[PDB]
Each structure stands twice: as C-alpha cells, then as structure tokens.
Amino acid sequence: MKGDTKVINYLNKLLGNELVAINQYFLHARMFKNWGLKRLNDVEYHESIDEMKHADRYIERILFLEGLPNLQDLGKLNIGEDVEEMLRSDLALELDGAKNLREAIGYADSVHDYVSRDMMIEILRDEEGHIDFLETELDLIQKMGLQNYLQAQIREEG
Amino acid sequence: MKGDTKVINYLNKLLGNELVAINQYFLHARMFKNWGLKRLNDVEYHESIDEMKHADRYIERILFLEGLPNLQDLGKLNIGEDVEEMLRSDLALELDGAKNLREAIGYADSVHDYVSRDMMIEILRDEEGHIDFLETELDLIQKMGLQNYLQAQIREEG
Amino acid sequence: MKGDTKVINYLNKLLGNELVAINQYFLHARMFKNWGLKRLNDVEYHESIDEMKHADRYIERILFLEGLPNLQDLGKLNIGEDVEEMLRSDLALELDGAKNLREAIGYADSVHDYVSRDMMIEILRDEEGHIDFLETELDLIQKMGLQNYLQAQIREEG
Amino acid sequence: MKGDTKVINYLNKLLGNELVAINQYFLHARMFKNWGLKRLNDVEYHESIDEMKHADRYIERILFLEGLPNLQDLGKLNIGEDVEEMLRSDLALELDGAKNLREAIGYADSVHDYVSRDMMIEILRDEEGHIDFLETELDLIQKMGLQNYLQAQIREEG
Amino acid sequence: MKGDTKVINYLNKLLGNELVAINQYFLHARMFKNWGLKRLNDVEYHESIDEMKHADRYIERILFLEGLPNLQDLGKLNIGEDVEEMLRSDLALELDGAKNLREAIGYADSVHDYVSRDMMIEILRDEEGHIDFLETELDLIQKMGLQNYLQAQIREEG
Amino acid sequence: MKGDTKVINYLNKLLGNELVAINQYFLHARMFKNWGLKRLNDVEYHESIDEMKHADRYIERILFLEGLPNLQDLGKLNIGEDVEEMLRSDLALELDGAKNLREAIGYADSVHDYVSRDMMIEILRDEEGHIDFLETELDLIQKMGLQNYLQAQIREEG
Amino acid sequence: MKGDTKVINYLNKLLGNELVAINQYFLHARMFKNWGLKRLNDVEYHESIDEMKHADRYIERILFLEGLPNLQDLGKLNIGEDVEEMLRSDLALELDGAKNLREAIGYADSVHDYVSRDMMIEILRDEEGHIDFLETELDLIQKMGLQNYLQAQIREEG
Ligand code: HEM
Ligand code: HEM
Ligand code: HEM
Ligand SMILES: [Fe+2]
Ligand SMILES: [Fe+2]
Ligand SMILES: [Fe+2]
Ligand SMILES: [Fe+2]
Ligand SMILES: [Fe+2]
Ligand SMILES: [Fe+2]
Ligand SMILES: [Fe+2]
Ligand SMILES: [Fe+2]
Ligand SMILES: [Fe+2]
Ligand SMILES: [Fe+2]
Ligand SMILES: [Fe+2]
Ligand SMILES: [Fe+2]
Ligand SMILES: [Fe+2]
Ligand SMILES: [Fe+2]
C-alpha cells in the first residue's frame, strides 16, 4: 500500500534512532559485564533487544508502505568511560528519540496514517519506560553514593 | 440489629483513620516504587491493603449495627519528601490511631458490644504490627546510615 | 521526566474522580451485601477494585511526570438510600468523570503527551463499560419491576 | 456436475432466506445483549450461527451444481422494538422459509436431485427446531407475564 | 478445676437457650423442607448444627469447671405457622439469647474467668451472624413480596 | 449513552462495508474450495470471520451509543470469475473501506468519541493486514506465473 | 589482560564486517517476508542472529583485551532489488569477510593470541556455512528457473 512519503521519512529517522540505541546499549551492556556489574549488563542488554524489536517494527512498516528502509546511516554514538557518564548518555539519547517520536506521531495523525501512529505510540510507551529506568538509576547513584551503587550491581536480580 | 450510637461514632472515627492510612500508605508505596526502592514499595503497599481490609470490616460492622458509614470526611494526610520523614509520618499516624482504638475498645466493653470490641482488638493487633515495622526501619536507618539503608531497599525480599 | 503542568493537573483531577468512585462504589457494594442483594455486591465491589486500579495508574503516571499526586481532596459522595437512587448516583458520577476524561484526552494530544493520552483512552473504555452496566440495570428495574429485580439479585452469578 | 437450473434457483432463494435470518437473528441477539437479557442473546446468537451454517451448505451446493450463488440480494428485515415483537418477527420469517423449503424439496424430488433434497430435509429439520423455540418462548411470555419472563432472561443457562 | 458457681449458672442458662434454639431451628428447617422451600431448610438446618456445637461447648466447659450441665429443663418453643412468623420467632429468640450472653460475658470478666468469657464472645459472634441472616431475610420478604420470596427458596444455593 | 449522531452514521457506513466484505470473502473462499485451491479457501474464509467480528463490534457499539444498526442495505458485490480478478476485487474493496475508516477516525476524534476511535483504529490495523495479504498474493501471481501460483494453492498451509 | 594492539584492530575490523552483515541480512529477510517468500525470511533472519552472535563475541573479546570496540563506523550496505541480486550481494560480502578472517587468524597465531585465533576459526566455520547456503540457492535458481525457485520459497520449511 503506497504510504505518505513524509511518514516514511519519519519512520526512517526513527529507525535511525533505534539503530544508534541498539549499538550504544549493547556496548554499554558488555562494558558492565566486563566490569562484573552483572545487573546492569542484564538490564542494558534487555534494552538493546527492545530497540531491536523497535527497529524490526519500523523496517516492516516502511516495507509495507513501499518505502526503502535505511540501515546505512548511523548517527553519533556517545559511549562514555564510567557508569554515570554512560547512563547519562543513554538518557540523553532516549530524550532525543522521544522528541522525534512526538513529532512523528502528530504528523501521522494529520495525514490519517493511524496505524503507523498506533505503532509509534506503543514504541513511545516503551521509551518512556527506558527513560524511567535511567532516571531512577541516576538518582540512586546520588542518593546512596557511587561505591554502594556499584556493589549493588554485582549480582543479577532474580 | 440496632447498635449503640456512640459505638457507631467510634467505628466511623476509626474508619476515618483507616481511610487516611490507606491513602498515605499507597502514595508512600508508589513514591518508593518510583525511586526504585522496590522493598519499601512492597511493604507499604501491603500495609495499604491491610488498612483497606480494616476499613471494610468497619463498614460492614457499622452497616450491620444500622448506622451510616462515613467515607466522605478525610483527615489530614502528611506525605513528606524523603524516606525518613515519610516513615516517621506513617508512625505518628499509627500511634494516633492506636490511641483512638484503645479508647473505643474500652467503651464497647462498657456498653457490652463485645463483638465490636473483639473485631477492634484484632485490628489493634495488626496496627501494633505496623508500628513495630516502622520503628524497626527507623532505627535501622540510624544504625546503618541512610546510604546503606537505601541500598538495602533496591531489591525485593523473597 | 518533567511533564506538562496542565497535564498533571488533569491527572490529579481525574485521580480525584476515581477516589470518589472508589468510596461510593465500595459503600454501595456493602450496602447491597447487607441487604442480601449478593449479585450487586459482587458487581459494585468489582467496580470499586476497577477504580482503584485506575487511581494507581494516575498516581504512578503523575509521579513519573514529576508532579505531586493529590489524595487529600475528596469530592462529594452521593450515597442514596434505595437501589435505584444509588445506581443512578453511580451513573451520574461516571458521566461526569467521562466528561473530564474527554477533555483531558484532547489536551494531552495537543501538548504531545501521547502516553498519558493512551492510558486515559484505556481508562475511558473501562468507564464506558461501567456506564453500560448501570444503564442496563436501571432499565431492567423498570422493565421487570422493582420486586422482580430485587429477587434476581439474591444469588451470585456463576 | 451440471445441476438442474430450477433447483439452483430454489437453492439461491433458500440462501436468500438464510441471509435475511442471519442478520435478523444477529441484531436481535445483540439487542438482547445490550438490554442485559443474557439468555436470549445466547440463544439468538446460536441461531444466527445456525443460519450461517445453512447458507454455507447452499453456497457449496450451488457451486458444486455449477450455478452462481447470489449473496447480493437481501430481502426485507423486520427488526421490531420490543421482545415479543422481535420474537414474533423471527417466527414469521421461519414460517415463510419453511414454506419455501417444502416447495423446493418436492421439486428436487421430481427432477431426481436426491442429494439436494436430502440436504434440504436436514435444514428443514433445523428450522422446525427454531420454530419450536420461538413458539415456546412466545407462549411463556403470555403464561408467566412479561415482567417474569424478562427476569428469567437475565442469567445465562448453564 | 473448681469454677465460680455463678459462672456455671450462667453457662447452664446459656446452654438452656441453645437447647431451645436447636429444636426450634430443626423443626423450622424440616417444615421448610416439607413445603419444598429447599433453601431455607439448608440454612435453618445449618443453624441448628451451629447451636448444637454451642451446646457442646457449654457442656464441656461446665464439666471442666466441675458443675452439672442441665439438659433437663427446656424453655418455651414458639414455632409459628407461616414463614414470616417462624423467622420472626427465631429472631426474637436470638435477641433474648444475645442479651443473656452480654450479661454473662460481663460477669465472667469480673470474676476473672477469662476463658469462659473468650468462649462466650466467640459464641456471641456466631449469634450475631444468625441475627444478621434473619433480619436480612425478613426485610427481603417485604422488599420483594412474599410470593417472589417463596419462589426464591425453591432451589438450594450452590 | 447517547452518542454523536454523525458518529453513528459513520459506524453504520463502516458496518455496511463489513457486510459487503463478509459475503464477498465467503463466496470467494468457497469458489476456491470448489476449484480445489485449498489454501485460498482457508485464508479467505478466515478473512470472512474477521469481517464478521468487525461487524459485531460496530453493531454493539451502535447499540451502546443508542443508534439503530443498519443491516438492511447491502452495497455492490463484485465477484469476478478467475483468481486474479477476484483477489483484485477484494483489494479494491479493502482500499475503499480503509478510506472510509480514515475519515471516520478523524471525525470521532474531533467530537471526542475516543473509544469509538480506538475501536476503529484497531479495525483499520486488521484491514491493513488484509490489504498486505492481497497485495502479496497478487505480486506472487506475476512473479511466479499463474500456473505455479495455482499449484501452490492445492495443499493447506500447516 | 592487555592484548596485542594489531589484534584488537583486526577484531574491530571483523566486528565492522559483522555489523554490515547484520543489517544487510535483516533487511533482506524482511524484504523476503514482505514479498511472501516465507522460507527466505526464516533463513536470512537466522543468519542475521548468527552475525549478531559473532559481533557479541568480538565485542567481549576486544573488551577483555582492553581495547575499544568500534560500533560507530558502518561499511557499505549493498541491498539490491530482486532475489538473485540480493543473494549475490550477501555472497560477495561473506567472501570479503572470509578474506579478512583468514588474514586475522594468521596474524593472531604469529603473536601467540591463540584464543582470539580459536574464536576466529570458529566464526570462519560459521561463515563458510553461510557461503555454502548462498552458493547453493544461487545455483538452484539457475537449475530450476526463477519462477519455480520463487514458488518453492512460499512455505516455511518444517
Ligand atoms: C482510595 C485510594 C485507594 C487505592 C489507590 C487503592 C488501590 C488498590 C489496589 C491497587 C488494589 C489491588 C487490586 C487487586 O486486588 O488486584 C486494592 C485492593 C483492595 N482494596 Fe483498595 N484502594 C484504595 C482505597 C480503598 C478503599 C476506600 C477501600 C474500602 C474499604 C478499599 C478496599 C480494598 C479491598 C477489600 C481490596 C482487596 C484486598 C485483597 O483481597 O487483596 N480500597 N486496592
Ligand atoms: C452478515 C452479518 C454477519 C455477522 C454479524 C456474523 C457474525 C459472526 C460471528 C461473531 C461469528 C463467530 C466468530 C467465530 O467463529 O469465532 C460467526 C461465525 C461464522 N459465520 Fe458469520 N456473520 C454474518 C454473516 C455470515 C454470512 C453471510 C456467512 C456465509 C455463509 C457466515 C458464515 C459463518 C460461518 C460458517 C461461521 C463459523 C461457525 C462455527 O463453526 O462456529 N456468516 N459469524
Ligand atoms: C548491530 C549490533 C547488534 C548486536 C551486537 C546484536 C546482538 C544480538 C544478540 C546477542 C541477540 C540474541 C540472540 C538470540 O536471540 O538468541 C539479538 C537478537 C535479536 N536482534 Fe540483534 N544485534 C545487533 C543489531 C541488530 C539489528 C540492526 C537488528 C535489526 C532490526 C536486530 C534485530 C534483532 C532481533 C529481532 C532479535 C531477536 C529478539 C528476540 O526475540 O529475543 N539486531 N541481537
Ligand atoms: Fe526503541
Ligand atoms: Fe529506548
Ligand atoms: Fe488499620
Ligand atoms: Fe496500620
Ligand atoms: Fe475509573
Ligand atoms: Fe468507573
Ligand atoms: Fe436456516
Ligand atoms: Fe431458522
Ligand atoms: Fe448458639
Ligand atoms: Fe444462634
Ligand atoms: Fe473488517
Ligand atoms: Fe478486511
Ligand atoms: Fe559472522
Ligand atoms: Fe556470515
């Protein structure tokens, strides 16, 4: 079914955001793993799979609307060298992605692409969950101190 | 069965205490949840359900004694902005409720409403359990320090 | 994540509606229970739990958006003294809450709070179900007469 | 296999009757459902599925005999506004369909289309069951009165 | 263990009340059974067993306290000839027994027979349940009318 | 609950589209079945049930909003005589229905009928799935040729 | 453990190859899915997961050897517009990656990084499997013709 062109560009831009998050979350996960911060590896990994699922949804949707999914262009990763910095970097990235999502959802509505919209509202809801997680971790770091926070990441949560 | 009027007023006043505790405990629970203090959310939540059960018992009793349960008037919530302050506020509230309970139990005895009394002694026993919990948490905060105490709330207790 | 201020006020106002319905439905339930109208106790009780779930969702959302959930202010209960009057009162309350919900959903859309909106559309759908139930019961009362209607509430529905 | 032409016209006319009954029974079912007459929704719904099965049989038979099933022409629905009127309308419709069935069965016999006949005798037997149901309900309405009859439809039959 | 004499007289008087209720409830049950009011037979029967359990408790207690249980004197039965009258008669009897129970509980307290008291408060709680049942049935009779009430007793409650 | 009048007209028009699709899909299914194209019978049949579910949802919604579901008027069926033509006809019909859906969804939003909207967005999502299926089949016919395509429909897909 | 620098550059270059293959295989998979070539979607998807596992292994190894995994630079995707072209493009990519792998394995040996080597020989073995698959499919296309080949991709392999 021939989709609206500008909807497809939004879908590709959103896809672009997910491709960045996939990589940044996966590296972060395995950095934590290497450092033995077992709990942060499990969570960041599971957020990486999340973004993968999101990318898949965009890709299928773009293809269905008869556009060309763009997996070639990869935006800026910002990795960071310590826990706080890296969590903070993931948070900034989610915030920028939520902004793009808000814009695309409004536009899909105005051209009547209600199913693209509905898929996007779902993804936003997942993002908003990732945002909540990061914000919470970052405040815990400050409330309990970095040393206690790190000790609390050594074992996986059952 | 037509109950003693003053017993019904006591039952409504006790109900009023429970309605306050229901709300204060539930908000507290979800504040802790938001902060990621998973363990305090589970406990405060389970104390909220507790007060709900208490309210239900009062409501059924009032109705049985042919009075009018009063769910319209809600006393002062005192929420607080940090863990200690909020736990302390729950403790003051339980202490005031135990006081009212002691008074009502004595009175139900003197007008021979032994089953109202028996229900109330049971509830008091549950309150006394909540009091124990709060007092213990508050002392732990001081003995181990706030930072260690907070770290200890991150995971739920199995 | 810092939410829009006016969205938070709407969320608190909606929360306020749920707190009223929680109490009015619960008292109604136990009044029916006392009268031995077993079936109406089961349904009204299950609608009380429903509103509780709604309140919880608002509370968590407000907290997530970094506002202060307001459980202190409780609007007017209208209890009533016989079945019809009480059902009718629940119906008026749902109708006013649906009105507030419609307004809040429109506003959340225009400030791009699509997830608050999505949660609210879900709640509205549940309300619309409660409305359907009350309207149906009220018509049954008239079609079959009060005496037959009452006899039909004595046993629980399997 | 090339069927007799007039048999195919009969099969299409019978199909036409079923298409009317499908719709009239389904709307009736959901009207009862809306009114909370749970038992009448279950029965009328199950009669709707019944007519659907009948339509399917005609369609397959017409196709097998190499004719063109006609699903385009839809006869007059007569919906009605209250229980009696609607049940009575379903009864008149079944009576007219049984008449057409009797005629078609005789004709299929005389051109030796014994399997079309055999399918039709089966369908007639089901119709005769629907007729029995409607007649019984309509007499119950008069014998026990409308109010008692309505109360008796509120719960589904196990 | 030698009990207080006046406690034993109270226990015998309470026992006397239970012996009356045992018989009155059992006859009532089987009257309802004979009339085909299956539901009232089940409930009144189960209240008869209840009073039997109460009698047993008094008997064991009196014996333990070294007194002589008195099963010889049987107070006035008031049977009645129709449903209302008979239910009303059971209600008056429970009311008189609750009065005696209230008096005995106060006295057991003042002579420090706390376990006799504790057993009696339990029994009172069961009586208060029987009172609730009778009051409810009697109001249902008036609210729905005798004819509808009777029809509602024909089948047992699952 | 009294719905917006124009929403009800949209719901009836959408219902009208579903009634057409129900019949066109069902005949198509049994045509394929007759031709021994087992796989296309299973898929088209399952799309017929799909439209039935959609019709049911509209009917219940219209009734809830207190309008009159219209099952009397049936739009133009376009059946076709060979596989391609028939698939193509189903595709044109879905495309026209999606158009009407897009329009109705926008309007329900502007009069605040958010639950009608939410139901409609769901249905659109199902339609968009049917569209995908038809488009894919039609391209497969061209890519692999009609003879190979037909052979591939002989067995059902596990 | 501080690894050899040039081994880390090889590991990053190999990682780079995997990141390209991940994306190219995933898009290819969902293109096939969209076209209804169910079997090629399953296989290409499962090769995408394969490359992901490979990337993960490189990432963990680089981190262990104390280098910086590079997920920022993405080489040229070559997508293609029809089955042959796309399969052929995957084949050229695997061939270039096998070449880089052969070179890296020899070098790891000469600096005594035997475990990096051992991981790489394993990955090469998987690549060599992908190469086999693509070569076989491409020959099948020629031996049986494109139309027959396409028909053979419609159903998934059990
Ligand atoms: C007003 C703020 C309240 C909130 C936010 C709230 C919330 C909740 C929640 C989330 C549940 C769990 C739902 C479930 O059982 O699956 C629950 C259960 C329950 N609530 Fe409330 N509630 C409130 C007030 C009340 C009031 C006024 C009553 C009346 C007495 C009440 C009585 C109950 C009872 C009896 C249960 C079931 C307990 C159980 O068996 O687990 N609640 N509530
Ligand atoms: C036009 C208004 C119609 C409505 C509202 C409607 C509705 C429904 C519904 C809700 C179901 C149950 C879905 C399920 O099986 O889970 C159903 C089943 C079915 N319908 Fe329809 N339908 C309609 C017309 C038709 C027509 C024209 C046919 C063609 C003969 C048909 C044939 C069938 C068949 C064969 C089943 C499955 C029966 C079974 O095995 O349970 N229906 N319908
Ligand atoms: C580029 C760096 C990537 C890495 C290191 C990576 C890694 C992984 C790993 C280790 C798994 C788990 C394997 C398993 O399921 O057993 C996985 C799963 C998956 N990946 Fe990736 N991946 C990457 C990129 C992508 C991309 C670009 C996509 C395309 C959308 C994608 C889509 C998926 C999907 C759909 C799953 C299965 C999710 C599930 O059902 O559990 N990934 N990935
Ligand atoms: Fe995402
Ligand atoms: Fe995210
Ligand atoms: Fe309490
Ligand atoms: Fe408490
Ligand atoms: Fe609600
Ligand atoms: Fe509600
Ligand atoms: Fe039929
Ligand atoms: Fe019929
Ligand atoms: Fe007793
Ligand atoms: Fe008793
Ligand atoms: Fe549909
Ligand atoms: Fe469709
Ligand atoms: Fe690989
Ligand atoms: Fe490979």
Image (cartoon, coloured by chain):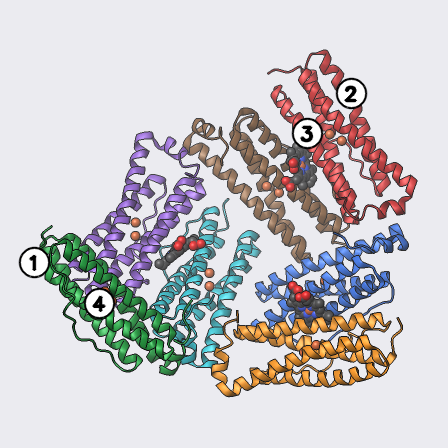
Chain colours: A brown, B purple, C cyan, D orange, E green, F blue, G red
Residue highlighted by disc 4: B3
Q: Nearer the viewer, mark 4 or mark 2?
A: 4
Residue beneath label 2, please? Answer: G102
**Whether residue B68 is visible:** no
Cα–Cα gap, marks 1 and 4: 31 Å
Decide: is A97 above or below E138. above
Separation of marks 3 and 4 at Cα, in angstroms: 76 Å
Question: Is G73 displayed left or right of E55 in the figure?
Answer: right
Measure the alpha-carbon separation of dots 3 and 1. Answer: 90 Å
Q: From where the camera sits, is residue G102 visible? A: yes
The chain that hosts pointer 2 is: G
Secondary structure category for the residue under label 4: loop
Q: Is mark 3 within 8 Å of ligand 3?
A: yes
Q: CA distance from mark 3 to mark 2?
A: 17 Å
Could you say which quadrant of the image residue G136 lies in?
top right
Marks 4 & 2, CB-CB < 8 Å contact: no
Tag 4: residue type? Gly
* Residue placed most toward the observer, D111 or F8: D111
Asked if residue B110 lies left or right of residue C118, the reply is: left
Q: Disc 3 marks which residue?
A: G55
Q: Which quadrant does ligand 15 occupy?
A: bottom right
Residue G10 place in picture, x, y as percent? 72, 20
* Disc 1: which residue: E5
Distance between the alpha carbons at the discs numbered 1 and 2: 105 Å
Badge 3 density bin: few <14, some 14–19, many ≥20, Cα 10 Å? many
- Tag on residue D131? none
Which chain's residue wears label 1?
Answer: E
Amino acid carrying mark 1 in the image: Thr
Residue drawn 46% across and 36% down?
A139
Amino acid on which disc 2 is placed: Arg
Determine the residue located farthest toward the left in the rendered image: E5
Residue type beneath disc 3: Ala
